[PDB]
Length: 158
Ligand SMILES: COc1ccc(S(=O)(=O)N(CCO)CC(=O)NO)cc1
Ligand SMILES: [Ca+2]
Ligand SMILES: [Ca+2]
Ligand SMILES: [Ca+2]
Ligand SMILES: [Zn+2]
Ligand SMILES: [Zn+2]
Image 1 (tube, helix red, strand yellow):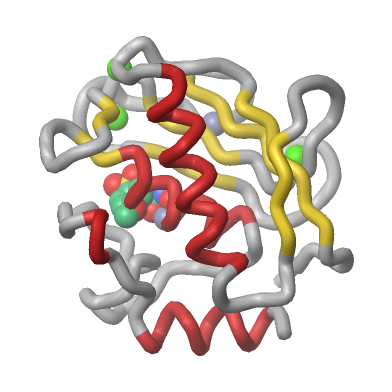
Image 2 (cartoon, helix red, strand yellow):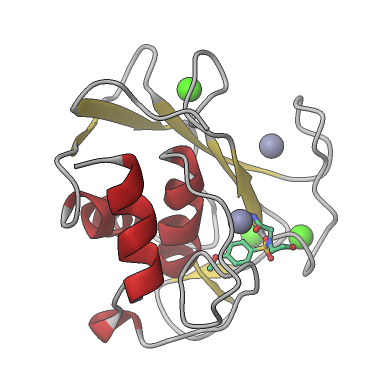
């Protein structure tokens, strides 16, 4: 599967969910990128204009890729593996209610998983892994990648 073949990766926040404070969306996305840069050689930088490697989008229903969202619940987000164009991009279902806490769907935890995909990771069968394809809230203040996540990302980078 594809990986980014460079060490400096850019992201851009296309638009902001009205569910959250702007600074909280910025911080959640920043902290989620940091989870992955903690365990690889990668460096992430937010850019404000122009083409980013990873475009972060909030959208509902049909949104121009061939992967429609389904309203509240069900699919929370999806992302594309490394590559040109839409490659790397992470889309968050605006029909969810995004939060900084245990209420609704936690943006940070969801973004960690999505950014895993943006970097080339697939799903894990281990319930403990952030890449396990089922959302279960865990306290984000003390979140940790599982050994499975670490093995997975280190098999792709570093
Ligand atoms: C913790 O992160 C997530 C992110 C999304 C989802 S999910 O949206 O519920 N999901 C699970 C399969 O239906 C689709 C997926 O894996 N997208 O990447 C579940 C957990
Ligand atoms: Ca949904
Ligand atoms: Ca892209
Ligand atoms: Ca919403
Ligand atoms: Zn999409
Ligand atoms: Zn997934």
